[PDB]
Amino acid sequence: ILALERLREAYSTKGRLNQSQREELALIEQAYDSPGTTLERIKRFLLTQ
Amino acid sequence: LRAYNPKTGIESLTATPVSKASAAQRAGRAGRTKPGKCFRLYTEEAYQSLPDATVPEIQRSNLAPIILQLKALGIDNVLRFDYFTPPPAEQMTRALELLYSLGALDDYAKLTRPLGLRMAELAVEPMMAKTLLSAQSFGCLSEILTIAAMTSLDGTLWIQHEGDKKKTESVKRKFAAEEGDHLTLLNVYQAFVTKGRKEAHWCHENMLNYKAMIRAVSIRAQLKRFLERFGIDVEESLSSPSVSQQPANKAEKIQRCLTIGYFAHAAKMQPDGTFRNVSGTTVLHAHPSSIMFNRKADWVIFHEVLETKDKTFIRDITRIKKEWLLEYAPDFYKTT
Amino acid sequence: KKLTNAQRSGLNQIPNRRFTLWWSPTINRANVYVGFQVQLDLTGIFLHGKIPTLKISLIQIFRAHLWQKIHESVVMDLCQVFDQELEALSIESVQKETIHPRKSYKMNSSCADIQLFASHKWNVTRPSLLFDTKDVIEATTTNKFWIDVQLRYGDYDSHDIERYVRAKYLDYTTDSMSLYPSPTGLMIGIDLAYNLYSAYGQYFPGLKTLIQQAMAKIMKANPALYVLRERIRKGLQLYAS
Amino acid sequence: RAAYEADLTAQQSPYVFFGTPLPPLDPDVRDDGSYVPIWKQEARDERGRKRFHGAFTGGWSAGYFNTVGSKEGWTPSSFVSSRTKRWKDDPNKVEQRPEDFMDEEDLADLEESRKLQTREAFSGLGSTADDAVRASGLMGLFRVEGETMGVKLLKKMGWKEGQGIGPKVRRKARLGLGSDANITEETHLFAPDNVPMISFVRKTDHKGLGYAGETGLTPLSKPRGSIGVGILNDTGSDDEDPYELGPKISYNRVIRLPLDGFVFGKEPDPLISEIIAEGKYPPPRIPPGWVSSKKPSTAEAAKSSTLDPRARAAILGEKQLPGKS
Amino acid sequence: VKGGVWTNIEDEILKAAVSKYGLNQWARVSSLLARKTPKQCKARW
RNA sequence: AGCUCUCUUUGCCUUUUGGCUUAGAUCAAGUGUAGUA
RNA sequence: AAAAAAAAAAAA
């Protein structure tokens, strides 16, 4: 929640987003909707990537 | 399952969990020829809180044709009627509101001087049965009689060809009318009957069905007979070559009669592409079979509204005017 | 939407135009250090210097001869007031004078646009303001009256319509360019930018209170002032509740 | 080039005898009727050129070419009256409406502000506005439904809200005295109760029955008005409030082996079990001696069917609703 | 959807657009494609 | 040996990318359905 | 010991 909140402070300002900002907002909303899959993805990224 | 909402007034085709009896029938449909197996995809405790039987069909349907039929039989005391399971107390209030708006009923909850009797015996949705009654006083009758043949029709005219995408649009554009989707159905009926010589292979290149639409031809004949028993003479000017009447006034006459009838199913298109009701509360979208899927309009009428999984679609989009609504629905709609 | 650069710049420019229209009495202020005073065409608005934002805002507010239409509406509604009040004031016949369609925005001189004919000699008083109470009736008698209407768009340093009507009566009667027929009359003044109203001139008995009631009624219920106020309200986007 | 689009429309859409045919699908001819999102639309005037004309609608001009006049000019209509021809009693009273002093833009905005809504006696599609009234407590106990007239016409013929429909139910009572069966049970005729409606939960997922699913996380909390900063300089709404920092802080006041993944049912389904079972109804006795007594158009009748519902229900034994008396 | 697995058709259109446009112009190359960003086309190359 | 025909090879450039700057600067997108006949 | 046009609104 804290990580996504500090990621929103850049781009939760409504209006005039480029494609990467909209992709970031979609990813943050997807992480808000399904936290467990996001956490498993993050831990897999820390182990492997 | 389909469930007509009583407060809003839209259908809802939603994925209801199956009943105990329906699941029992589904299980028992397996072992017919040899002993089979059943593979219900839920837990055993999930088959413990399911409904024992399905929801009554009289509790999740539009009661306005039913109240219409009951008053056609003469039983006007629909409150005191021996129902098998009684419908819930405010769905038929919406039905009676719909029947009063569609002529038919007076202020005293009675079927009127044969106006109500003429909507009583017709096997059409009462909305455009009201239109067909309020057609003869305003000229054109046979054209929306044809549209009445096309509307009372479940399985669609066009054969769904997934292999053709631009070709399906082009053959839908072969009979296309900018002034709504009903005139396209009128055009394809006139193409089949007058010049097509009742030929099926011509419909086979035109990506159209044959059985349901010749059934619609029989339906148009039956409704012509029904209005022959109404005492109004039939004005079949389609066979005559009298095209001296201008067709623009004829087209706006047809859609003017339609919004005389379909004033309840009125919507306005919004800039974001979606439609919205007159109350401006619920989001409506164009059905991806109508002619106005990509076309821009301001005010529209639709034949029927249905709720899919998430989007609420409306079918048979036809262009109208706002002052038509303020003129032909003076007791239903009022300006600010 | 896909907008061109000029359309984008005008769209960005709109809030500045609303701000300038809101603060226009102190922006189009009469007491300036320098600035060539120019009358806006077909209106009575004097602009000091060139402020294009204020000019385009005031053109939008006053579209399609609205200054002339306000003048015409005021003189016609005073005409219906005098028409419904012939009997109490012994008015013989009332008509409004029309040769110049330029009188509304003519600040150099003026004409008479309402005339009253007297069946008997009226003992008019001294020229006095519309709310004066120390009326002094003199021995001079008259047999004809005129009513003149003066529109004005004031500003922050000049919106005293009392001094405006008094000085314009003292200036517009002794001047020979003005063509007032009768020697006795009354001039009303309407400040549009502040919705003020006054008058200066003689009074036969029963005119002052009638003019008071008619002036209150026309300030609260003018159709042309209603159009002006609605255009101003849309320009500001300042709504009520 | 009008002939090319004309006979191209004739070739592409030959059978359009009702309505207006669509413009042809070609790269040369644009599609005016097609809806092209909003982020693809261009701002055009009545004449099709890309410009604005108002001061408050983003134009660099206003009025009649930066002038408050008109091409036709202005002419003051006259007014004469007297004791003989008085203005007040003339038949042709041309009234001073607030539309002689307006313009076509003013009338367009006036009809723009004039919206459309349904009447009070009729309910519309999708009307959901009574929840705020009802979910208020003592405020909603006084505000009752404003008598949509279908409820009124049901009220006239013998219905009161709070109860369902059907034939009248002959149950005695409940008095709140527990479940005492010692009442005389003389069974007044009550009214049928209201069975509730159904409201199916929206189902877009493929998640099965009895599956709770993953729960979500909530975001970590969150002279009126002012002259705007512009619809394009609103950027990310950089301005919220100068006088204090951050959002509004909300405060507390305290401080056979089956298939894989499939289990065997511990009990069989009863409903399929009575299919092969003998059931709970013994067949009729059928003694010897009984004998069968019976030894081994619609359209034309409907045309001659003069039985109106006033006389159709007379032979059906039904009581007609009371009318205008 | 912006992204996804890369197909052979997308790969060949990427190679053709690189042929016609070069390596310092990725926005045009992504504009030939439909589901890939300029950065995704550059990463695939 | 020379002259002509066809072909090959060599030479051939035969029209064989007018400049500059912050790669001048930027640049996702409508929709898309169908218990029951 | 007391300071007030242009870009920029486009070739029968």
Image (tube, coloured by chain):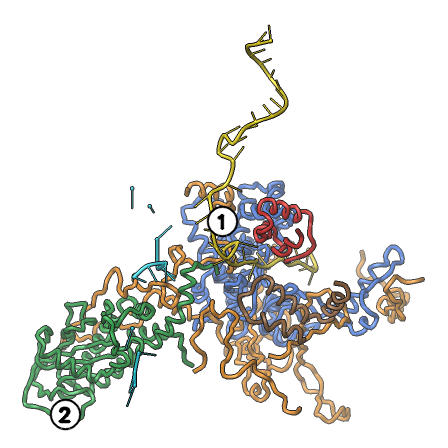
Chain colours: A brown, B blue, C green, D orange, E red, F yellow, G cyan
Q: Percent from the top left, x then y, of residue C214?
A: 23, 83
Name the residue nearer the viewer: D94 or D187: D94
Crowding near the residue tagged with mark 1, few <14, some 14–19, many ≥20 C-alpha atoms within 10 Å: many
| Residue B142 position (above or below residue C164) | above
Q: Percent from the top left, x then y, of residue B306?
A: 61, 63
The residue under label 1 is: D22
Name the residue nearer the viewer: D179 or C151: C151
Residue B72, quarter of the rendered image: bottom right
Q: Is residue A29 left or right of residue C30?
A: right
Q: Amino acid at mark 1?
A: Leu
Residue C135: numbered disc: 2
Q: Amino acid at mark 2?
A: Asp
Chain letter of the residue beneath label 1 in the structure image: D
Crowding near the residue tagged with mark 2, few <14, some 14–19, many ≥20 C-alpha atoms within 10 Å: some
| Residue B238 position (above or below residue D49) | above
Identify the residue at image location x=14%, y=92%. Answer: C135
Marks 1 and 2: which is nearer the front? 2
Chain letter of the residue beneath label 2 in the structure image: C
Q: Percent from the top left, x then y, of residue B300?
A: 50, 61
Q: Pointers 1 and 2 in contact (CB under 8 A)?
A: no
Residue B41: numbered disc: none
Figure disc tally: 2
Name the residue nearer the viewer: C118 or D88: C118
Identify the residue at image location x=57%, y=85%. Answer: D140
Can residue B235 be seen here? The reply is no
| Residue B248 position (above or below residue A43) | above
